[PDB]
Image: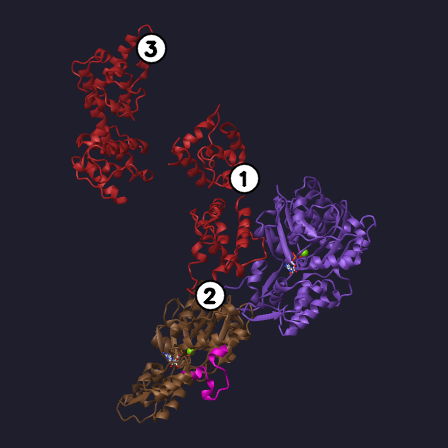
Chain colours: A brown, B purple, C red
Amino acid sequence: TTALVCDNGSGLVKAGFAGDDAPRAVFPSIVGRPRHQGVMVGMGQKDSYVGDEAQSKRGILTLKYPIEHGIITNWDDMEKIWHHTFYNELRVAPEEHPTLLTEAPLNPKANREKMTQIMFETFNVPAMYVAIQAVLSLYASGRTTGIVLDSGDGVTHNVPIYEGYALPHAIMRLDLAGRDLTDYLMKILTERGYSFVTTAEREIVRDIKEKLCYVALDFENEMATAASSSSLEKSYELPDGQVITIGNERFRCPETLFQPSFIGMESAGIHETTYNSIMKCDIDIRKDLYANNVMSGGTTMYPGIADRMQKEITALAPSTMKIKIIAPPERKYSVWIGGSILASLSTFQQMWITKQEYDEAGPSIVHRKC
Amino acid sequence: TTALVCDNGSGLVKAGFAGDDAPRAVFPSIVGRPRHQGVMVGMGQKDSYVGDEAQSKRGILTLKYPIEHGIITNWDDMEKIWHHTFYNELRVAPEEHPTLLTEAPLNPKANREKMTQIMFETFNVPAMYVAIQAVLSLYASGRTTGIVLDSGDGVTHNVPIYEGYALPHAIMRLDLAGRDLTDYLMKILTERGYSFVTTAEREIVRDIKEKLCYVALDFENEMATAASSSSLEKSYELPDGQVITIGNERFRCPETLFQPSFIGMESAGIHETTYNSIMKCDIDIRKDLYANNVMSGGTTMYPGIADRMQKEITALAPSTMKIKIIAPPERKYSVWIGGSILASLSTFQQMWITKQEYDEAGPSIVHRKC
Amino acid sequence: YSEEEKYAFVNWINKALENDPDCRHVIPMNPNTDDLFKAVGDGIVLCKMINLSVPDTIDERAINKKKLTPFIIQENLNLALNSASAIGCHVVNIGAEDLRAGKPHLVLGLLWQIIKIGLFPEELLLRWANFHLENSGWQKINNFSADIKDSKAYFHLLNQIADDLKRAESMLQQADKLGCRQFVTPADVVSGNPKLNLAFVANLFNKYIDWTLLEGETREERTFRNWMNSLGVNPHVNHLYADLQDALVILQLYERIKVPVDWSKVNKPPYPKLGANMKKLENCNYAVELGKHPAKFSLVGIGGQDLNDGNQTLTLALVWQLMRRYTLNVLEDLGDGQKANDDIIVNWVNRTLSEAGKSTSIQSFKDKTISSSLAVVDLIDAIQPGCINYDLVKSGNLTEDDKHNNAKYAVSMARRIGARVYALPEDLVEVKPKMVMTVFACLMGRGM
Ligand SMILES: Nc1ncnc2c1ncn2[C@@H]1O[C@H](COP(=O)(O)OP(=O)(O)O)[C@@H](O)[C@H]1O
Ligand SMILES: Nc1ncnc2c1ncn2[C@@H]1O[C@H](COP(=O)(O)OP(=O)(O)O)[C@@H](O)[C@H]1O
Ligand SMILES: [Mg+2]
Ligand SMILES: [Mg+2]
């Protein structure tokens, strides 16, 4: 019939048909369960909440993410999310559609084998495929050469590609992303006396981060600007109607991407990680990688992120190289767009792992076909 | 119709039509193969890169020269290069053109037989001929008396000719040429910390050699000059924008031609080899040989090479002889130019090995007719 | 620097590669565009070449229907280059990685293999090219593609009509006169590719009616003589009362109005010196007999001696009835049967012009809009699209006097297309409903 493209991110689920230009379903990758006594008749009859229903009823629920750092850690809740995706958000029978899934690089091999077994046995898909998220971001952009910086909710990774060849030895991966920035914002919000401690309040801090945070082009004078003047302060309204104000945490939160030591990590920032990934590549392709820095994922949506990456990589390159960062407005769905993109190609229709192949090699067939 | 002249050097391929003043096609004699993982669908099913296209995509390729020291060592890649030169760079059907090939002296006989079999069975050219490169270099100068010093990428050889007669017993051959100077420049570039190790980086060092190296008129004075002052220092920019600087290595590289002991060889320099070739000739013709020292090939293009050869041979001559060095600006194509001159002579049209002769005597006919 | 240098290469490649019918979907259609490099680098022409002898092969949309995404457009280059079993690229040195972008030397010479294995109205202007092939006596080549299949008959007839790069001059010698040297490469001059030889020889020979008024002729007389000439009688009738005296032209007209003539009773134009007057008298008597009984004409007080003596009243009495009969035949043969009508034929031009869509339309043959030739010139090219020829037409800027020129132009080439118009231009310039109707009827004769 037609292929399905499900980009199971850590924080959000992107799903839809191949050939469309945007995911049909975009919902949080969460499962909610009740935490209070059912004093009202008929309201207590539902034991689990999956999609946006878990987010709207979070005041009486405990929220869990089935994926952390791009690794599926709860498989039964992941199956709840997959059933919700196929049968409630897309409303399709998976037995009729080949399904294209995505994954981060340098991931454990069992994650890819278990999701292959789940699609073939629980959902009985006719065929399936697992693609690297950063490669799909190139499939989204316009390019067969370039280094991709992907930053979603769980993982930040860099993949350099030249003429459709990857350099795996130069692939970088960092377990620092949006969820860690939210947790850091939660910690620094206590300096003003705000406290957020439940899982529901974590979603409130996520909304604050997505609404009032930005990347400073220079952190030291923004710190002085916020220390002297009030012009950087902004207000946010809590669900009970209380109002909070932040004027320094707005850029101190996203600064962790460039200074991971704010959360005790020894690793270098995303700019240095991109530069080191380029310097591991062959010297004859570095000029073309310097001119093609593709940004992808929701964590790359901060205002000023591309300008700061431009300034930092320029500060690291040999000056003669023309540094260019590409940051399309659809950065939030580049991986999904690339998946629907790849799944449409007629040359790809033989690359699917069919169920007949899986019946011979088992779940290990995914390591050979993908 | 029109004969084809193909001078298959170790480093460059020179091809064209008899009667023309310059080769129509001049491309590197290399074959490139992918060295990295393909990740984008149907980008990568190309197995072999050969001409300038193998040089432009060298950042993802392993480069192989099919000819070493004037011997064809890979006959399948050599067939690829001959296919390339006949159809892509010259753009002709070989069944309609007699082909003139070149060869170094004192070469293995099977090399000449194999190229004859290839030209008559793979391309089935109507006729062919294999000529000595130094003889063609004499034709390009219009002379009929003189000793030719040919130095290309793999072989340096001396051939004395008087009144159109060669002296085969005085032919001398040295397996030291431009490629060995490149590898020695790579070896001595590490003294400043510049490391080049891939086959793609060897092309960069070759470019550095062709742009910054020169022959010292007195090696010990240039060494003392570079040891005292930086006035010999010069800079080169790498493809990633790094800038390297060399002073002393500029002339220590080409000095190996006069002092082969730099690369561990026991053989004498090109000046002594030329003098020894003259001293093996009859004493009555040595005066005419001393006045006609013809150089050819790209390795004879270094600044100061003719002044150094003039001074070195003058130091070896009986002083009463008038040493003359002939070093035309077209030195890089003297072999091809002389081959187009020879192939355009009406008297040469009966010297072609025809296919009828080959169909009877086999590949061994080339030893009789050439 | 040079803004262009290789449009001739595009033409040459088109000439040589037209052996495969589908290759022009990648290489240019002979307009000298640059679409060749990118799609040839994908190797699409390699799989196209199978369509040369057998179209039942890899279809253009079966291999590539743009299932190549907007940003990764890698896939098709390998899918089409892997099909190089056809023709075969010797140059086993390149391939898909390099041909993704292409290189000039690489492309030029892989095209050289393509050239090496690639090879193993019009007739109206072509007849003035082939008439000379008859010489003392031989068959005609027509175009240099249909009759000739090898150089044998071609050279044999060239001997009477007098490296391929120099052999093509043998055929281009008749083209040398007007400078038609290029755009017809020697490969297809020798090979005889059809579509190239059709237009080349047609356009080469493209440059290779009496509407006067006499000092004393009425419009009726001029119309009679005009239809005499238009009907194609063998003598060129200049004077009605001077050419019909032998009745030979009248007997010819009888054949044209479908009245049978027994020429064994007709004395041939080579009359013997003795009795020629009697022979002509016999012919006039036979013509009168054929005009009275089988033609059914009212000829009271007319005898053969009247036509022999050229009596104008009785001769006009016959030629106007000839007009009546011929016009009736022209109105009836357009029908399914004996019917003749004006309003079933006047709307035909209005509805057949809707096949192309032009602003001419006429309500009746008495309409004043047909005073200029715009309506007829609009209708005259609708059924024959090869005669558009709006070079000499006038529109809106015409006066009373200049419309005579376009009226004559449309009436003249009506006979070129095949409409047997037997009308004077004045009969079209004026709103004479009895004759413009015949003009339209003749245009409809070739129409349906
Ligand atoms: N405009 C924005 N500003 C800051 N952070 C954002 C913005 N949009 C999304 N994010 C963050 O990016 C993450 C979601 O990005 P996404 O690419 O969907 O990750 P995943 O695919 O792993 O679910 C969340 O942490 C979210 O808070
Ligand atoms: N200007 C130059 N200075 C020094 N070396 C040169 C120069 N130009 C070419 N060369 C060297 O000469 C060789 C060029 O190849 P060539 O002389 O054609 O040998 P072959 O005929 O064996 O291919 C290479 O070793 C190249 O590095
Ligand atoms: Mg994600
Ligand atoms: Mg050489």
**Quadrant location of the N terminus of chain B?**
top right
Residue C383 versus residue B170: which sits nearer the camera? B170
Residue C183 versus residue B14: which sits nearer the camera? B14
Amino acid carrying mark 2 in the image: Phe
Quadrant location of residue C129?
top left
> Which chain hosts label 3?
C
Quadrant location of residue C420?
top left
Amino acid carrying mark 1 in the image: Leu
- Expressed as whole percent of the image width and height from the top left, the position of residue C261 reads 29, 19
Amino acid carrying mark 3 in the image: Tyr
Check if residue A267 falls in the magenta segment: yes
Residue at x 31%, y 38% (from the top left corner): C389
Are the two marked residues, 1 and 2, in contact with CB atoms closer than 8 angstroms?
no
- Expressed as whole percent of the image width and height from the top left, the position of residue B262 reads 73, 68
Say which label, 1 or 3, has the lower sequence index. Answer: 1
Q: Which mark is residue C165?
A: 1
Residue under pointer 3: C271
What whole-number distance in Å separates the C-alpha atoms at marks 1 and 2?
47 Å
Would you call the spot at circle 3 few (<14 residues within 10 Å), some (14-19), or many (20 or more)?
few
**The magenta segment:** A253-273
Residue under pointer 2: A348
Residue A62 shows in this picture = no
Residue A148 shows in this picture = yes
Check if residue C179 falls in the magenta segment: no
> Which chain hosts label 1?
C
